Length: 207
Length: 57
Image 1 (spheres, chains in turn blue, green):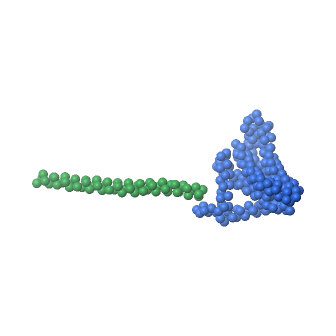
Image 2 (cartoon, rainbow over the protein chains, first blue to last red):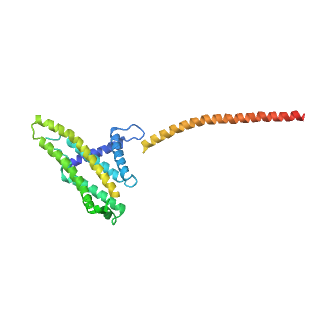
């Protein structure tokens, strides 16, 4: 699973290399420039709509790297490696690492904003003082929600591919084709969901 | 920020181009109006001095 992560890491790093080479503000942009710009302006508008760029700028690179990372992972899972490659999120370790890092990131940013002595009580009291004990469970559920959702869906995709493999090849090609077709879509949608809920949890952690 | 600066420069420069053309016309016709006012003031000042030498003679 480490190498399955490494291949998507080097793909994203090569795309950053390609952007660093190709970038032009005066001339006509390339395909990788329009991709990076469309993703960055989307996440930038998202964070502006809730917290404002001036209060939490540090969330944007995290959001965009999460999105590209897990998106390229899911799309790479589609390539015809069935016979070594499998989607990395199928391992609990991968999604656990990502979600735990994002949790510690936004919680440490909230603590840095309000103070170590101030932010925990503000978070527990939350939107309504009557909901404080439910607010505890919601705050605890946020990282578990992210991790278990992403892991469950991509693990389900891997298991479904391995199950479809059971068919004979002439039967096999049809459910495999349909499943990978919609798997591209669901993987993109879930990448968007993960980055968007990251942004929104940052937002509500700030206030 | 630089693609925004191209749109800002293009819109500002087009607006200023119309403003600067309007100012080219206004400055030329205002200099001709000042020149005409000075010409008619020098022509009427010559007639007034001419009337003065007429009544002095």
